[PDB]
Amino acid sequence: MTTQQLKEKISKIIDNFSGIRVVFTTTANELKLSRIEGSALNSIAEGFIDKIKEDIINNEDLTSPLLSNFDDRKNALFKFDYEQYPEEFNKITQAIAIPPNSQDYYNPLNKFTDVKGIIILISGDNKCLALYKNKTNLAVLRNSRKMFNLDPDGYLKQLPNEILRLDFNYDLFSIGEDFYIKNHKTLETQMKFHQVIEAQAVIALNSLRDSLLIEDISGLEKSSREISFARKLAKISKHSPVLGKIDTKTIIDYVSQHKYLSAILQINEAGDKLLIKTKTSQKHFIKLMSDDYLQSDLTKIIYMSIAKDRLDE
Amino acid sequence: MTTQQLKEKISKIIDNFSGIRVVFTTTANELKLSRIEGSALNSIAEGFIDKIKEDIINNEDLTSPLLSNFDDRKNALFKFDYEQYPEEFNKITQAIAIPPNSQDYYNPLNKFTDVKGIIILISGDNKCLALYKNKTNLAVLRNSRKMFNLDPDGYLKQLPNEILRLDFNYDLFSIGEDFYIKNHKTLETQMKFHQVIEAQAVIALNSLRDSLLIEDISGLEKSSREISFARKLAKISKHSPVLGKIDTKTIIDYVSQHKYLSAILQINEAGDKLLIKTKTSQKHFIKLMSDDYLQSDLTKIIYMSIAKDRLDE
């Protein structure tokens, strides 16, 4: 389901906006309905609709690649292509379909410390888009305290620091039965997705040691505890057009002949394995199995692709 | 000044943290000093240090490219390489150097509607890093409203709507005499940099007209009122490895041979100029002069680089 089709689904919901209702997900994994005032609700609706337009509708550089094809692209919504739905995904699926007559409402004596996330149900064209935000530390919003009598020298101090936020920023959303991610840190941390990524990264590490391309993998095994390397290891494990496709000797000779790659990735003292241990050399070898080292067919200049897309498909 | 040098400067300030003091910049372009309570000041220091570490120190994939070399890369702090300092740049430069004994303090009767931005002066290793935050449009809170006496009759509703925010999110910062941008929308909008960008885009249009490579520029001028195309026109005007090379016939033949481009970028009946009228053809020609169409010398697959880095340095 292409990016343009995502745009037309979003515009069908937006331009036929039917209603908005907000679901709080608690720490006990029960969807408690909210009690947002009508005027604030209209303001919320307006702001979030504008945010959706700015990020999807009028966003011409909006790209929809796979989450397992993780790269560094701003204004990019990743398609969730994994088999494992963290419990909040199922909670959002059920959040789509609380019947309107339900009295399962959120008691506000909970002081908004039970609030674990916030679900914004924007409905349109008889469909229901669902946004998810989290309950961050309340940015520490300090207001001037003018205790005095009722203070031109007062000082700034957060008073309640229990007030709900929703700074108009979806971390992820779901249309139909298709989930999209904007703030990946939320998925890997709050929803505890790092397990899946680290397991796929271990699969990649095993394929690398079994491929016998490098000499000492303890460098990569050390770097695999960080998630910034685990995502790239998972990307290589699931999408590498180099690992498992081109033979090892061709890769060794490619590094040898490639002037820059040889100077960036040092070659082994023998010549059948590679010596890749330091953080930068690890990152370069990672970008090597990612096929990010590309030469121009016009200007004949080599580049370093942070984000790329196949054109033949 | 490379990215690693930024990393060691930032860790020098962080690991030798000496103090933090906050300056409010008003709408009249005068730096009024703040009155943040000590504990809240401590929370600010803590949170902003964590954000700085997460975005610079512990960010292993942090890139520091030029602002005029704008591409779509997350975890990237753009180096301000223009000659024109928007007024807030000078305001931050002067914010670095308010003497500690200054009593030019912000009177809080202003209800924080005079607050135009917020300057966070994080000092360390006898240097002063300076963060800048603004009041983003898409920002809102909600507190519970309910009372009766002091009965489930009440709703959630924002009431003060004057409270200062300072989400732990810097839009840009300045170390020494080197400015870096994170939230580019803040620069192009609040600081009104879009004039400079549109001027560079008109310069690019003129350079394209002088190149005599295209036939009709009316499409480009229509799309140039949008800023998302103006940034790409500025990138081509200052960095294009294709524009500025007088070889239109070579580019024509390249497009002809290029399997993908030939279907999108049509050649005229005389074969000396290009036919670029539709938005899609415009976007493809833009990514063409950006040298984003790159073929692998290993997998022999053509790709579309959203973000790239020249490797020669």
Image (spheres, coloured by chain):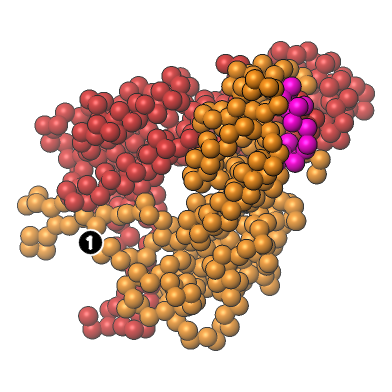
Chain colours: A red, B orange
Nearer to us in this view, B187 or B60: B187
Q: Quadrant of residue B173?
A: bottom right
Q: Amino acid at mark 1?
A: Leu
Left or right? Give the position of A199 relative to A77: right
Quadrant of the rendering where the N terminus of chain B is positioned = bottom right
Label 1 marks a residue whose chain is: B
Nearer to us in this view, B249 or B144: B249
- Stretch in magenta: B240-254
Q: Residue at x 44, y 25 (%)?
A: A4
Query: Residue B37's spot in the image, x, y percent?
Result: 42, 74
Query: Residue B43's spot in the image, x, y percent?
Result: 46, 64
Q: Is residue B248 magenta?
A: yes
Tell me if I can see residue A218 in this picture.
no
Is A104 located above or below residue A240 in the figure? below
Query: Residue B38's spot in the image, x, y percent?
Result: 45, 73
Say which element carries label 1. Answer: loop
Tell me if I can see residue B274 in this picture.
yes
Q: Quadrant of residue B310?
A: top right
Is B163 located above or below residue A90 in the figure? below
Is B168 located above or below residue A25 in the figure? below
Nearer to us in this view, A144 or B63: B63
Q: Residue furthest right?
A: A270
Query: Residue A137's spot in the image, x, y percent?
Result: 40, 53
- Name the residue carrying label 1: B159
Q: Residue at x 37, y 65 (%)?
A: B164
Quadrant of the rendering where the C terminus of chain B is positioned = top right
Q: Residue at x 51, y 31 (%)?
A: B279
